[PDB]
Structure formats: structure tokens, C-alpha cells
Image (cartoon, rainbow over all chains, first blue to last red):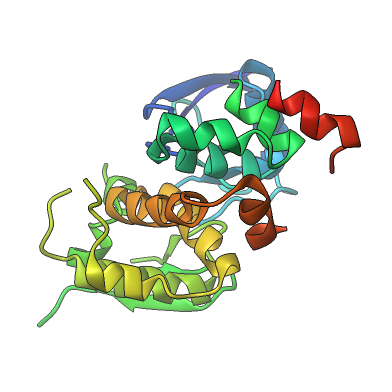
Length: 82
Length: 35
Length: 134
């Protein structure tokens, strides 16, 4: 009852963070808001300062990964917003 | 929020003398220059 | 006879801009690695246009007071929109716009007393001003 997802990042310059890819242990029933909070636990950035995009569509905060067909080993570029 | 990382970035361009006066502006700025 | 990508703004207004200038934002070109509008979070459709005018002018640049003349006149805009231009140049990873806009705010802070700095953009006790001087 648990999958593995990676979420590559982008080069942020106001926050001196190099582009990396965080690895997550989630479930397809987890909402995008949940997996945003699962990023909060390892780093500390609130979900209201995160943006997930799988292919070209912004991920809504009230739908599970099954809605966007997010399978295992899939990469979701995350973007921080102030 | 939104004011920390943007204001800390404009502090890098200001010389060491300008950051000295920047602490007397506000407390939120005073806590930022000392980090 | 010209390459074009769609860029959906935060408001929802889609922008058809050339890839050669969208490649100026390294987040957009890296987003295409590995036929839909690329999202621009926290970047309003109004600021997006202001972002395009700076980029489309700097299309021929690969990456001591170094403030450009046209850019400093391009940044003769209200303080509110200038802050909205710094955040975007971080989301889009625009090293030229991130520096020109940050150096201009620092130019607005430089050369002024702390009260003159606060009077431009705006909470102390009476001893807090003396205690901060220590």
C-alpha cells in the first residue's frame, strides 16, 4: 500500500537551492495536497508554497494521483511560489 | 511569507555600510541582517 | 514560419510566445525535457507581459554600477509591480531580470537614512531605536 515517486526541482535563486529531485513514498490515493505535505516533512516548505506539474498541467490540490494517472517512478517537477 | 527571501537578496548588493543602517529600519529587517 | 509555445498565466490567459525567448527562462526550457500551455505559477498575466518585454529585449545576451539604461527606464513602474517582477524572475529563473530588479530596489535603499528607507516602503519601542543602535 505504498509507491515511490520522485519530484525534480528547478533552480531557485532567491532561495539558494540547486535543482534536485526529492524522493517520496506515497500512495495513489494520496491527494496532491497530501504529497505536498509529504514534501513539507522532509524540508519544511508549506504546501501553499508548492506547485506540482506532471506533464504540462498544474496539479489541483483536491485530487489524488490516480486522477492525473501518476504511476510509480514518475517525476513531477515542483515549483515554489511565494 | 514573501518578504524574507526577496529583501535578503537586495541586501547582497548593498555594501557592508548600507546593511549597518538597514537594521535600524524595522525589527523584521533587524532579524534578517543578523542571519 | 515561427516557433511558438503556449504559456498559461496564473489568471488563465494563455500566451503564445516564441520558444527562443521562452528559452530565456531556464525553467520553461528545462520543463520541456524528457502541445499544451506550460504553467507559470504566481506569475500574473499582467506581469507575464512585463516579463516578456524585458526578455524580448534581452534576446541577445547569454547570461561597478551595471544597471542598464533601458532597463532602469523599464523599471520606472510602481513599487508593487517591481516586487512582483523579482519573484517571477526567480520562478522563471531569469538571472538578468533577477539581478536588475534586485539591484534597483537596493538602489532605492542605498544612499538614504533608515527612516528615509522606511518612508519609501512603509514598529519600534522608544528604546528599540536606541537598542538597535547598540
